[PDB]
Structures are given as C-alpha cells and as structure tokens.
Image: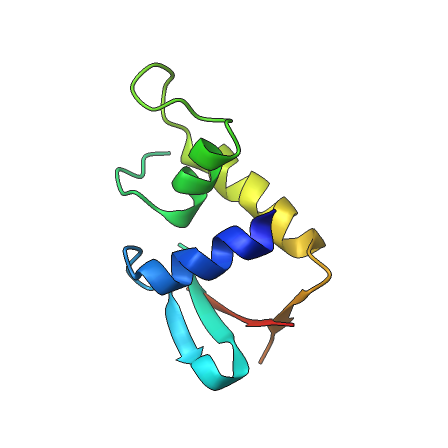
Length: 91
C-alpha cells in the first residue's frame, strides 16, 4: 500500500524536500534528517497506517521514521540510488 500512497505524496508537494529529481525517471528524494513538530512523510504515514492518532496520543517521530524505513526498504518496486537526503527510483 506504500507505493500508491508515496506516489501521491511526492505529487502533493505538501512535504518540503519531497519532490521529483527526474520525474521522467520517477526518481525522487526524501529528506532524511526526540522532537519533530513538522507534518513529515513519516508522521503522515503513521497517521495513514493508523499507528498515530494526532492529538490523542503523544507524537513520536523516532518510531515514525523507523517504521517508514521498514515499509519503504521492503518495497520491491522501489530502489534506492546510492553514491541528509535519500534518492529513490520508482519501478
């Protein structure tokens, strides 16, 4: 379920740093950066997967980021391009 969701998130542009680097190639970029106030991809992914209920349980970005890294790293159809940001290609 992560690949369909992630595609629209890059598209929304409502996540600073989360943008296409080569839209033709579906190559995009995630800002990989215990308090984070911002509405990051990790937070909204925890919201969407039902694992964070804003305002009623206490924010926790360490776990948001950890759990997003598990989902994204286990996608077979998303590959990381490697040599504070990660570059991925949709496939």
